[PDB]
Image: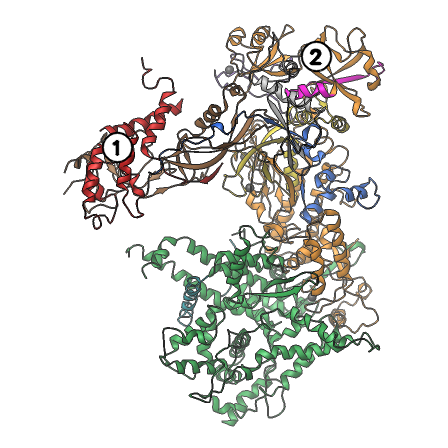
Amino acid sequence: FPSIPLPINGPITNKERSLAVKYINFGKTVKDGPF
Amino acid sequence: EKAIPKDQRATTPYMTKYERARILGTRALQISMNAPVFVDLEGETDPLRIAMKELAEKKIPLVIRRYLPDGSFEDWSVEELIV
Amino acid sequence: MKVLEERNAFLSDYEVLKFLTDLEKKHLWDQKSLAPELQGITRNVVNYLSINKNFMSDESFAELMTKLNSFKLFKAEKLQIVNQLPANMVHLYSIVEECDARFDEKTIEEMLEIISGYA
Amino acid sequence: YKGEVLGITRFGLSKMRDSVLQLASFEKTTDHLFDAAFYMKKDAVEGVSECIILGQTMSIGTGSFKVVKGTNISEKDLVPKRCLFES
Amino acid sequence: FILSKIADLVRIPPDQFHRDTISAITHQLNNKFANKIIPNVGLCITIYDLLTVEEGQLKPGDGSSYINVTFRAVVFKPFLGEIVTGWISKCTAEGIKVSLLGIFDDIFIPQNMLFEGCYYTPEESAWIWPKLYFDVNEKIRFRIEREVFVDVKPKSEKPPAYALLGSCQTDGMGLVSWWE
Amino acid sequence: KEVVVSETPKRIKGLEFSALSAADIVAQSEVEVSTRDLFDLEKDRAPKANGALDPKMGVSSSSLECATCHGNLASCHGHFGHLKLALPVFHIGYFKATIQILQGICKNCSAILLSETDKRQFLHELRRPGVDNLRRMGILKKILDQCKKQRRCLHCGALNGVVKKAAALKIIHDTFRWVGKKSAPEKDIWVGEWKEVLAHNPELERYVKRCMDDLNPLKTLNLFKQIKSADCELLGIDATVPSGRPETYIWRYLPAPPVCIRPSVMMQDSPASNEDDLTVKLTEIVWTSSLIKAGLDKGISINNMMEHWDYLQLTVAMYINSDSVNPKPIRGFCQRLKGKQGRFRGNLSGKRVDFSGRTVISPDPNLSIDEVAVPDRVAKVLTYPEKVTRYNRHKLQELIVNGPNVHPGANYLLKRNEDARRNLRYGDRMKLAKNLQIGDVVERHLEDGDVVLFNRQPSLHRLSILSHYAKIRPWRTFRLNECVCTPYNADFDGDEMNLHVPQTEEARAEAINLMG
Amino acid sequence: SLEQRTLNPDLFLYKELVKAHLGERAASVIGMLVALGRLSVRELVEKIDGMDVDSVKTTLVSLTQLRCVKYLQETAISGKKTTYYYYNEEGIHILLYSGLIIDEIITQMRVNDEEEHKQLVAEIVQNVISLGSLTVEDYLSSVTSDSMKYTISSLFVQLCEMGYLIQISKLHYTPIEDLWQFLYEKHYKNIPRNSPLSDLKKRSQAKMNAKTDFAKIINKPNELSQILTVDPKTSLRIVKPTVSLTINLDRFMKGRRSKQLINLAKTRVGSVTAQVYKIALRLTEQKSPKIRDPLTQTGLLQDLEEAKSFQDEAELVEEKTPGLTFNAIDLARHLPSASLINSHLKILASSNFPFLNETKPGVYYVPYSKLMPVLKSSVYEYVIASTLGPSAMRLSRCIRDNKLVSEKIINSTALMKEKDIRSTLASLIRYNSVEIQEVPRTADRSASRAVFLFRCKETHSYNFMRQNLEWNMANLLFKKEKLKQENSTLLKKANRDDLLPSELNQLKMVNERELNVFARLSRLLSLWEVFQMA
Amino acid sequence: TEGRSRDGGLRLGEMERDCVIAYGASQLLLERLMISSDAFEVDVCDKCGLMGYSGWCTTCKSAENIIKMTIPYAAKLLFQELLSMNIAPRLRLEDIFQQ
Amino acid sequence: PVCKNCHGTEFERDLSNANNDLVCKACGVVSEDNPIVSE
Ligand SMILES: [Zn+2]
Ligand SMILES: [Zn+2]
Ligand SMILES: [Zn+2]
Ligand SMILES: [Zn+2]
């Protein structure tokens, strides 16, 4: 319903798909931690 | 802030002007909803007039719970009141 | 509408007949006036469990409960096996687990004659 | 009774009692409504002139006390049917 | 066959003032709690006793007597492993409609704990067996694992209020006449 | 179903007011009124497409049906519609309170004009338990005195002067308070931009001391939305509710009231319906907002649309309170809650009621005090509900067989299972007399023994009303005993008084023992 | 999603980010703190509903360890001591930026190649801040007795003494305004009675002494001479082992700032000079002017005679600091030729973008106090040129140099057709990049007898879109955990094994779509972080 | 409706509301201002308390927390046109019993 | 238009007793009382 997106809508590159790995295991570290 | 027994009873023992409009007010609705009355009625109608006759023998099966303004109880059986 | 607690205690299946037997008493000559909704449900309970018991005094019920619950702590299942296929040990094998490797004594033969003596 | 002698005008009624359904029942109506929800006020319904329009049992007069029925029972038959719990 | 400490208030019509209190509070709670389900508890049958009762209050618009009380009643919660012999009244092509005859019939129990030759044969049979068949109106032994409780009404039959889970994992399951 | 249903009767402890959010409007509305025109030229009876007297919004007639809830007029409680404004406007009720919310805060960084160790002292006076409304707004007077006496802000150092009305209904901020030092980083940039435009069209120098930067309803929403929630309680509004943010106090969406509030009255001089004042005020704003929304999309002049956006700003402030016309005046919301019996005296404090009557008075000595005499032609209209019991079963059976043409009779009855009423002038009575289930209620006429209230209409004091017994006489006028005339100060010169009759049993008892 | 898009400031970001990977009991407590400001635990209890008094303290000590809030104590004279609790602005940024801390360590530290701690130094950054505060003895007591611990212990002095691993204390852990309070009256009570003259000048005595100390107190954690232990046996250089430390974002934010400038370099110059500009900046990343500027955060920012003094000395810090003014003879050896490093640096002075602009002949240094507003003016304009037409880029720049333009001269300065600009300019009114100035020809602001002037208004024009991205940072990760609410029956199974064939596919389609999220979260993170240079 | 040809019905005024209140009466004042004249049946919600129709809340579309009461029609109609401008009469409910 | 028990189709507005109700001749059950006139 709303138009005009941001210009950053692109296929993920191999420069940062390894960087996206470091997020999800960081959340699995802390949430499976003490708290 | 709870029930108050007979010893620490510190208000009037008197059945006030607003009591006999409410007790008689709520009794006639019970009569009109087919609750059985206790007194020796003759042929009467008019469920109010059967109530204020039955008040004269002091056989109301009720009890008034007066409130102190601090949210505390105070109880008085309707036979213990005098008019 | 407040539920304070759900599982206060248990109640044995004799009182399911016994307390309901007195409920069958003061209900205007049940089952024999053929010549509300609460009546029809409350008779469907009493007949279903009694046929299982058929196909008595409460004292003789009581001492065979004392002999049975010889467990250390894991006993509570003695309440549910009171009328469920009497005189059958392969029935009792599939009810409680880890008893085929613990009841290798003369207990499990002694428990059989109590249940068949109840029959 | 609130520290200073004050009239019975608009300016006076704003300083005695602050119950916004009663003040709207007075002369200037909407000027006490918008600024009530602007500050997000909160009043219980205990005065008489707002128990009228909500339509509830009035707090005063013969609406002070309540009517309680005798229950003609004591503890003499309030024991359970406790029998044969676990053995 | 267990008790549950619950509390609720109950009204009294004025024409039951002539009858005594304990029978009156039992009667009006019976037809409220006769053949009813309880949210997240189970199926209440009949009021057992009366623990403690307060004083009767009155609503001024109605004029009847309204009373609150605490009491426990009987409710059928066997166990999560209870052996029981029910009956049957229906057979379906993906499971089996085994429910206790006499009381309630809102039960669908599957067969997910049995062997590898289990399907439907439309010849009044369950399936073809690798053995005495079983049919309507006879004692059929089945157990219980779980139950599902939902109390949501999406206003705009499969009644989902009180449905049990059953299986027939061991031998002798499907008919009680296979043993004894 | 086999499921228990149980509820207790409940009460209302007290109201709390709030402004509902800009997102809850579409949450509680369910239709939308984008289009304009009220009646389609289909030549149908109820021609309404989407944005009109909409049949799934409500129904303003007796012969149609509400397509949302259901029912014609007995059942439909009405439903709200919502609009969508093109670009925001001010709220005329909050217009007094939308400038107190701005005099405290910075016009550049949108922070409150306080120091840190000073603001912590103030809201301490909010947190103590003993606070009533009279001093809670008392300390809110001091919090806006302290801010406007402080010239420059705390986060970007920007200048901040004063802001007030422009005596339309827009507000302007004077950021110019120089004392004797004009060497300010605000002032040098102000002249630095201004001589650039004086190069061209240089006729404009006589306006400059008048001209001043404004705060339109678009940038004030962007100024309110910038602010943090931490300083909210210091200037009146609080957090912990979804609608507590202070951007909701100006319009962005407005709700449409259900059509029972604005009934389509037919004057019955012509087969066209004369619609009330309130629809065409809401109708003309969806036309202005639609052509503004089309105006920026195709492209229209900024010197043209700024008065079209001034128009609905002036127009929506008339839908609420019609005193801001700056002048056959249209009736508004604020024009009917207040005033000479609009609401709160003519419909909510003092109401209009059923079961009354009104004739003139004439004296009579021969009847006792407490005994008002009621004529019979009014006495077989004013009925009284009365339940059936074994104490009075033998009377009601003889009374119901009389019927409503002889005097001691009834008019209506309710059996237990039926739900509406039973008319007694129609159908068979004697067969209906025979059943008379014991839990039922009939409506007998007034007879000698019931309870009648009676008062003069100009009521001086508390004792101008009092209640009497009734007894029926075959003449036509009200008669009372003479000794009670001195409270009524009657004078028998053509005045008339009314009579009342309660219709419960607990009011029948209370009227005697307190007003006999 | 209209419920959320309307009544939610940055609180909609802060509430869910601690709700993302941390317990749910603590997401509601700091939502109460940010909403209501500051409060004690004693009256925290009735603001929330459903958390017991001790259950707050267990929840609050759970949130304390990650350094996500900041307490402060004041006592009553007749009363006991009370402890207020604030919200920490940058501690919650750490678990926001937590993915990007990992990728910078490898990129700043290129001295090692195919090391056996590639797994471990990325684990150590995940091991220094995930548990919260951390000291030396807590990681040698792991399962590894030695496993060359002396290499790994001495690895950190290379990794800590470059910065951004400063010993933790109470200084950065208590707020700055309240830190500025109790040192102000102490120097105000250092001067007693009987110094009578110029009472309005005697307030400056504590005020000038505050600035000298307030720089020294913030330098105490920056003081690196007290985090060393030169061990005379078995070692050459090691940190003090009894030191509790965490990450410090101050170098990281400056390092992220230098990551932003090289992109602006690669746009305004080709490939050869962009490689030159990156090398010289890395040498001066460890000591730079502060990006947060805590001295301008709070204080006497009201009056212009001091508000100008917050950048007069701050500029004078930048050019007169010995640790960055490079002589352009050091740079030729660090690249993997004294004429070329003059020639490629000569054009940095020629361009009108003031980086390496002004200098003393022979030395060179880049300024920041007159640079990053051109960076703020750079990333702002092209985003407008992306989200709508490039004609809107043309109208924006026409109002930049020409201030307060009317509707006749826009056709004289720029040149497009007349009907098309109004279908473009009005789009820029709606987003608060252009403004309205009104001039009345008649009395009482009569709308028809008026023309309408414009302005840039450089301060409102950024603050709109910064919250338009903070909400956009907050909107997309709501679809992260909401996506985890469905398909929850198998992620519990996928966390249990450590295998149905058809169910494995719907674990992949919920995997590459959230893989797109963190890439789309990173790209607008850089477009946002430029608006923190205040 | 006012008017003899409009089939009448009397206006019980505002100082007549002042005339009853001095008698201390608290029951026939309620019936003559709600029951005999203007009685109306409203089902209202508990949480986020504003009105709803026959079986819903239509702002939290759950239709569970519904508590039936009765109020005058002149009190319902205030609670809608006052909601037409942007102020909300949020209702809050207690039970009568267990004082 | 259709009664609730005997399903009659004719309704006769009685206007003698100032009620102006709606009721059929067959059985005597009212359809809708309290008429709503548009003033
Ligand atoms: Zn509807
Ligand atoms: Zn500012
Ligand atoms: Zn609700
Ligand atoms: Zn009929």
Identify the colour of chain D in the image.
blue
Identify the colour of chain G in the image.
green
Q: What amino acid is labelled 2 in the image?
A: Val
Nearest the eye: F279 or G16: G16
Which residue is denoted by mark 2 in the rendering? F378
| Label 1 secondary element | loop
Figure quadrant of the C terminus of chain G: bottom right
Label 2: chain?
Answer: F
Which residue is denoted by mark 1 in the rendering? E87
What is the x, y in percent for residue F374?
73, 11
Identify the colour of chain H in the image.
yellow
| Label 2 secondary element | helix
Is residue F511 highlighted in magenta?
yes
Q: Measured along the vertical axis of the image, is residue F461 above or below residue F172? A: above
Q: Residue furthest left?
A: E130
Residue at the image position 75 percent from the left and 55 percent from the top: F171
Residue at the image position 75 percent from the left and 12 percent from the top: F372
Q: Are marks 2 and 1 in contact (CB under 8 Å)?
A: no
Query: Which chain is displayed in red in the rendered image?
Result: C
